[PDB]
Image (cartoon, rainbow, N blue to C red; front, side, top):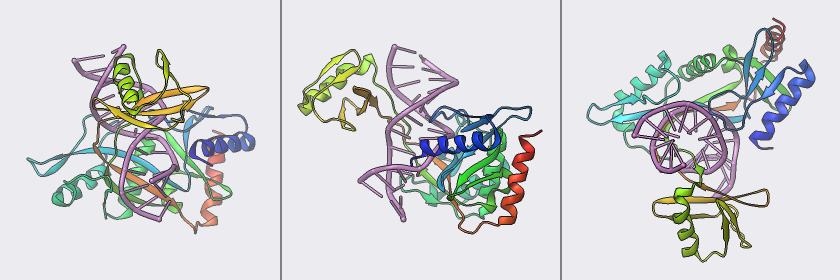
Length: 258
DNA sequence: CTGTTGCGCTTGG
DNA sequence: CCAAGCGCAACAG
């Protein structure tokens, strides 16, 4: 299943097993965490697939100073582990200053990255993670390293899309016409008997993406922002202590009972 | 009202 | 399986 279905699967399990106290938040909403527990001890739960990413922050190369600057537009604050990562990258500036989509790994001790994750998720009011290897695994954030291997890379990650808008409509129609596509439009709604699902076309410095939903097409404008972020990847361990697993399930049971 | 950015999410070439 | 990015919301203008 995909990540959206996986999160629903986790919420269904939580409500079935522990009562109707858990709610999934909006898909792709970056301002909140995946699952909210309702109770006198409220907290969020992150659902993670076995191979997932797990937080980021943008760094801007300062070529005049040969160091990295923490973006003032980042949505979490510098913690001591952020600072260790920035120090390593800045002291190795020539190795990281040339940004790439392939990414440059950061070979610091894994504990630095685990500690970043623990601080970051604490700051988001996330007390537990849920994952699955065929059975559901629920654990408190302080035990993260017993469940996931963590790595960290610095890579360009293009920013996301936006909806086609009225101002961009002439440019979009011009791009369609140059491609020879037969279509009509009612406002921002596109109609075509051609097979244009997931089609990419461009014009006047705009890259468009045509998505099919309902009974017609929804057009997106892709970003032109290509900044680079430190970003964490996690891989579920194949060998997890059953002793830790069982005590962590009891810790979850305590948290929802407070 | 529009375009930019950073964070969500593993993904699919 | 590894180089790579779109769906989303807050922001500034």
